Image: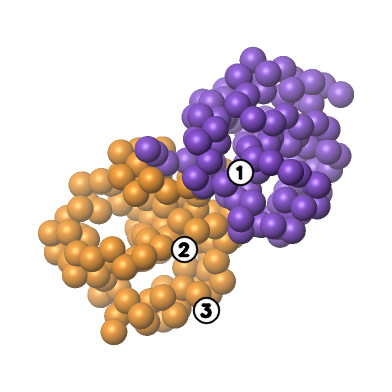
Chain colours: A purple, B orange
Amino acid sequence: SNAMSLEKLDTNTFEQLIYDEGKACLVMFSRKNCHVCQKVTPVLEELRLNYEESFGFYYVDVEEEKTLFQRFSLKGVPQILYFKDGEYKGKMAGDVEDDEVEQMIADVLED
Amino acid sequence: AMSLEKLDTNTFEQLIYDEGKACLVMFSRKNCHVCQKVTPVLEELRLNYEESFGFYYVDVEEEKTLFQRFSLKGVPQILYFKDGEYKGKMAGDVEDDEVEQMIADVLE
């Protein structure tokens, strides 16, 4: 019923941020019309406010960015992938709870 | 970040709807890597047009209700207007030829 204000990545900027800059972040691979993605979106927007510059919160549209989707061998949507220092650190799928995402952020920031 | 004039909801309505301004509006957010790439494309282009064609921006955190109206998925998005019509949009990173071509289609 609504809008999403996460920064939308194409392959290039994904490469820049996750690989070149080694940004500590999460990336939701999603589709525009996905009902579950629509439930997960607000949870990530709310979390972004808690970690403003310390951790990135990005979005990849898998219909536009098919190469990236397939780079990760992903087979469903929504999925949230976690990165720090250019490494792929973790992944969760489906209707996540903020507890789960928060713990992963903390696990990631710590290594 | 340079020439791009920031609009609040009130001014966005006055220009686009009450006055029918021909313009583009970049919907954006602070600390946005992709926004940082898109802004200089628009600033460079701006030089090629008279002030009759607006180049504007809106901060989605400040103009929440406005942004929600269009139910956009992701930032940045650039939306194009003329004579009070909403001519269309493009989303995420853009090249200058996409913007130029859209501007020409809007103006014709």
Determine which quarter of the picture holds residue B66. Answer: top left
Q: Which mark is residue B97?
A: 3
The chain containing the residue under callout 3 comes to B
Which residue is found at the position 14% from the left and 64% from the top? Answer: B19
Give amino acid for label 1: Ser
CA neighbours of label 2 inside 10 A, class few (<14), some (14 to 19), many (20+): some
The chain containing the residue under callout 1 comes to A
Disc 2 from disc 1: Cα separation: 18 Å
* Tag 2–tag 3 contact (CB < 8 Å): no
Do callouts 1 and 3 point to residues on the same chain?
no
The location of residue B48, given as percent across then percent down, is 41, 81
The location of residue B34, given as percent across then percent down, is 59, 54
Look at discs 2 and 1 and give the one toward the viewer: 1
Look at discs 1 and 3 and give the one toward the viewer: 1
Q: Which mark is residue B90?
A: 2
Element type at marker 1?
strand
Which residue is found at the position 55% from the left and 66% from the top? Answer: B94
Q: Nearer the viewer, residue B102 or B52?
A: B102
**Which residue is situated farthest in the left direction here?**
B18
Disc 2 from disc 3: Cα separation: 12 Å
Q: Which mark is residue A30?
A: 1
Q: Is residue B59 left or right of residue A30?
A: left
Give amino acid for label 2: Met
Disc 1 from disc 3: Cα separation: 28 Å
Judge whether residue B75 can be spotted in this image.
yes
Element type at marker 3?
helix
Q: Is residue B100 above or below residue A43?
A: below
